[PDB]
Length: 270
Ligand SMILES: CSC[C@H]1O[C@@H](n2cnc3c(N)ncnc32)[C@H](O)[C@@H]1O
Ligand SMILES: O=S([O-])[O-]
Ligand SMILES: [Zn+2]
Ligand SMILES: [Zn+2]
Ligand SMILES: [Zn+2]
Ligand SMILES: [Zn+2]
Image (cartoon, rainbow, N blue to C red; front, side, top):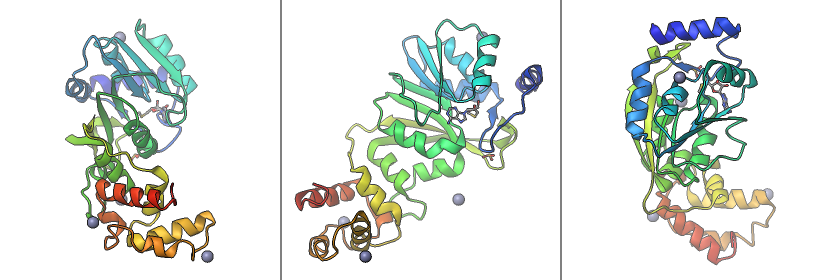
């Protein structure tokens, strides 16, 4: 009630509707916020990236614990409310689409993630140098992020998560926890950078996972013909490709790496 009332009061004070769009929901539970923050072990030395501060409930908690918070927000009207409603010495608001603007240097991310950017944000983050991220997604998307090779929901996002991160779902978050109540539950995800990162070619993985249900001979032939190359000058090389008895969705990052190295050696991806 206490944080839901306070939301209701802010929205009417400014006279703004709770969403311009349809993949956006406001965390209105004090203890989930404080749980996100204790899971990330935010300390007086940390420099934190937040995305989509909304009405700044999470932001405000981060500002009182961290050295510096950078928070990225697309809606210029939200930004004006944040500036009038709060008095942080150590918060830097960046107007922008979080998927497009240059990110600050940070050592951690503590953030609710607007669900519409769940995928693009995650790929961008997995390619950053951060100590620890604690982030909220829909539960379906979080189950994808920890899907195992050869399982039915395993996809490009799963591979890159496994290849580049250690990913833990920390707990379910009930739909009661946001306004307006989502139609499915969310999940609090911990991501640390993998100690021994497997660095894979983006174009290759996109190629392979364009249709992840195919065998890897098939997947490779199609993607490289689509680029504009002859089929005849590609067939024989592809049919000594390693892991060729797998469908793409069954591939470990290690196996994708061998396909890369193989294609690299035959000058296809160079
Ligand atoms: C976290 S759920 C709500 C907040 O996310 C913000 N938001 C939505 N989409 C984006 C985006 N692409 N980049 C940054 N902030 C966003 C909205 O303005 C809202 O305040
Ligand atoms: O609108 S929410 O359910 O993505
Ligand atoms: Zn405050
Ligand atoms: Zn689905
Ligand atoms: Zn053709
Ligand atoms: Zn194999």
